Image (cartoon, rainbow, N blue to C red):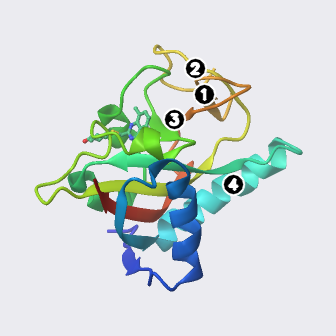
Amino acid sequence: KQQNFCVVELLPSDPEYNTVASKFNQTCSHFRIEKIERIQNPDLWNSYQAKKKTMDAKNGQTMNEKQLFHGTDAGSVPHVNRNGFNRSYAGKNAVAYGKGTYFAVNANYSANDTYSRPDANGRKHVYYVRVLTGIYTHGNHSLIVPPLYDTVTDNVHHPSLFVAFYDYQAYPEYLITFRK
Ligand SMILES: Cc1cccc2c(=O)[nH]c(CS[C@H]3CC[C@H](O)CC3)nc12
């Protein structure tokens, strides 16, 4: 009924393409990028920005937003484009640092075939996501919510991973379609 969306392909000549490709290529330059798409979900965006506003108000100097990677299967792409990373989708993720959605600092982490499952045509899907990491601590497998902390990480001093527990904590801004 809501969180309708549009999928807008970036021209390789679009500055936004150059920018996403760069971050991706820090760790995944051995992959070939077929396409980069912007997900335009105004309802999902506005919800994310409301959440951001409240967090920015409470965490003081903290830079609350990171751009992180999320590998998924072709079949979850329409679900994530509409709903973002909601509670039912969290159920589908691993549970190492809690029951939420997992995002990687580095693309190579997400580019694994366990996360970005190659589809029937060998294409893999990694979103480049705005995540409200805010104030985070070390996570563990029992958590259904953060212990509140905004997110949890594998390593507070040197994060590789973040887990978000709340709806509207992440915006799936870009979808990278690639192959081996
Ligand atoms: C646990 C974890 C650690 C690090 C990175 C990721 C990441 O990048 N992606 C994912 C979702 S994996 C996806 C879930 C839906 C299913 O149907 C297809 C597989 N998890 C991650």
Give the residue at mark 3: 165
**Number of the front mark, 3 or 1:** 1
Q: Earlier in the sequence, mark 2 or mark 4?
A: 4
Secondary-structure class at tag 4: helix
Secondary-structure class at tag 3: loop
Q: Hey, which residue is sitting farthest right in the picture?
A: 61
Query: Residue placed at 51% from the left, 47% from the top?
Result: 27
Residue 169 vertical placement versus 20 (above, below)? above
Task: Determine whether label 1 and label 2 are within 8 Å by CB.
Answer: yes
Q: Which mark is residue 51?
A: none
Alpha carbon separation for disc pair 4 and 1: 19 Å
Query: Residue placed at 65% from the left, 53% from the top?
Result: 51
Residue 109 vertical placement versus 39 (above, below)? above
Secondary-structure class at tag 2: loop
The type of residue carrying mark 2 is Gly
Q: Which mark is residue 139?
A: 2
Give the residue at mark 4: 52
Q: Nearer the viewer, residue 86 or 30?
A: 30
